[PDB]
Image (cartoon, rainbow, N blue to C red; front, side):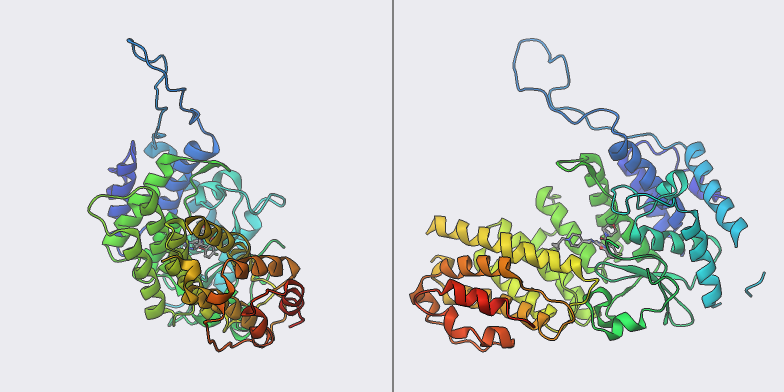
Length: 464
Ligand SMILES: CC1(CN2CCC3(CC2)CN(c2ncnnc2Oc2ccc(F)cc2C(=O)N2[C@@H]4CC[C@H]2COC4)C3)CC1
């Protein structure tokens, strides 16, 4: 049953009606995660899954009369009636409350597994786990489909609906599970990970193996407010690969600012980075500019998570790169590799591997080609060259002694090209200490007047 204070806010006819519902729920000790996620999923379904009116803008013509069709296209909002949303809410709570007095303010491992099994066993047996728009309880209720972290959110939402206030969402930079118990020290896997589960297990073994997936234990223990922030970050504006709903972007943006003003992103580095990326494209007057927010996310990760997160520096580097700040982008990537070098590359870390691959083999090559077209230039600065080498040193040190290889011949092709962007007289100016055995073993090749492509390929692809 929905409280009477929640009912009065309906119907939701605009983004700001949604913002006030979130504003009202965040003021309470337990924001209703189920209600909020259903509303977002309903809105997302009718703005992105079943797009009622296309986003096409007609060809810019002019004439004395008005245009036959709205010349800039249309934005819209699907009205969210209380009857529709309350009915879906009642469906979910009727499901969970009926499915789980056996368990007498701490939750047992047995209880957490049962709630987790209720969600798990409701899911469709065959669907594509990486589709868009299957993150919300609206998707669970109306489609019985959830993506990987959506399972974990739904398990937490189910635990809240049974009054299990010690069960919270735990988040790494690519995985989700639950924490519970007297001091939040109990852990349980509740979903699968990767393109291929450990359900029921603790995360002790993943923390001990020092994989990026478990962040060496420096992962996010959410409270109820950070769980709202997660569902907001989980909004997917994509209508197709090349088209985002303006409405859903604007909704996510205003909701992130709402959480920001209430202080609920203080320990959420990726949320601050996501907000900065939104401000970069659609700046809000009177708000901090994106660089301020990127540095807030880095400071958050230093303050609360031992500076063991990767993405805060990737957010910053990408912004510098898109704004042609070559020195600052290369430095931020050198800082990114400086964090990863203390991790072991394990079999479930493909996501951060893919981001590093894109940086090394597409983003940096483009940044350097751009700088060469301009050509003081960054390609004439030995500090930029040294930042490039430190980036590769961190990657090599990451690989070194890891159970999974990192560098392959394709990486060496782009390294040789990037080295070539710096003239030999520039490269011969650096005097650097490397950490990785791989980079130590080719320091001389990196600063030689002629770049020996075949020798660098051999060295970069040497085993371990
Ligand atoms: C490389 C770049 C960009 N890149 C940075 C990395 C994110 C994509 C863009 C930012 N995302 C996150 N934002 C906020 N909270 N969690 C995020 O991540 C997860 C963490 C644990 C987990 F189990 C699943 C996800 C996950 O993937 N997500 C997305 C969105 C929220 C969450 C659930 O829905 C899908 C991932 C420059 C820094």
